Length: 340
Length: 142
Ligand SMILES: [Zn+2]
Image (tube, each protein chain N blue to C red):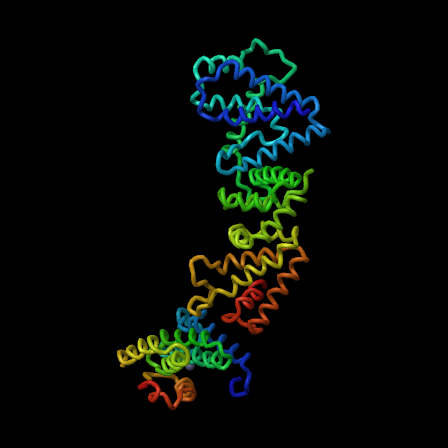
């Protein structure tokens, strides 16, 4: 049990340095040792992989290793990601050692003949390394071919494959850190937001708030993250299409009064010109009449627990800004009218 | 409704006048559909001066409510509309002299002196003479 610690950390070291370009001394001995360690790990995954305290202990070791590294400063190393990556750790190492250019000639020959012995062992009960790589290559091709022949960017982002997928990747990674309780998820998410492409990220979170629960801790963390950071939520609410954020609301009543707040204040910072009978903004970045109309359009074609909310938030802002009954005058009169 | 005292329904009616001046054309004599007013109602004069009229009429109700930025918007538009009224420039310049006089005011002074009644219909001529202030030239030479 404690025997497994020194084994797994040593293999984790070797796995991280797998990618690294120091390889002159390495040999058949290193390679054979690596693959037999990986078989041992893959064998444990099979033997006592479920319903054990050793299971949870190894995940403590994983997460605390993966947070002392962070993804910051010395190496943004992926690492073996979870206990299920135990089942194909061999594969990680092997793929990465192909990618290692510095791999010396005779070691590479012994390597490739140890990975690819041939059809001499065509008969195996155990899914050997050759068959494992097979199924990978096949799938990889498989995904290229579907993407480029019959894939379509679904409008309804919630039901897209890729958005659905990236959402569920994120939620695994959040559930781990939630249970670990080492750092707050807030920190993790804030750092993500700063590091990677924001346009993608937002859309995903969006899609993640909508997937039903799988083990709603995930959604319940991200809403508190978002209410915590208004400034990202100002670009969130601005960047997406309308129906997405509308069904976001009927799910999480906690986002409704703030979102209507955002536009309520976006409405008031226009001005109507009589030459073109249209509201317009002063600066380049001020939301159009059509995008604002759009968003309130969607919120009205929704469930009754949001209809009354949006209706009354507009009536109370109409009365506030003179209860006129004509255009030219109140952005809010314009809306109420435009709905019939 | 101004004489009666009703700010609300006043600004209503000025806005409704303005909407049918811009979000319609009076000169659609594409189809001779009837018997119709040749003269009094088509004159480009009657358009630009009727715009100015309702824009100032509404600007005064904005001044009454204390929304002098909106009043400035309507007065600034009427200046672009009919630059040969001077009732327009008068109201605009009095508002600038209330708030932020110098550069704006002088820029419009030099315009007036650069600038320096053909067939206006009667109810409109009469309406302008009604609303215009006596202390007009006095203010414009200051
Ligand atoms: Zn006529």
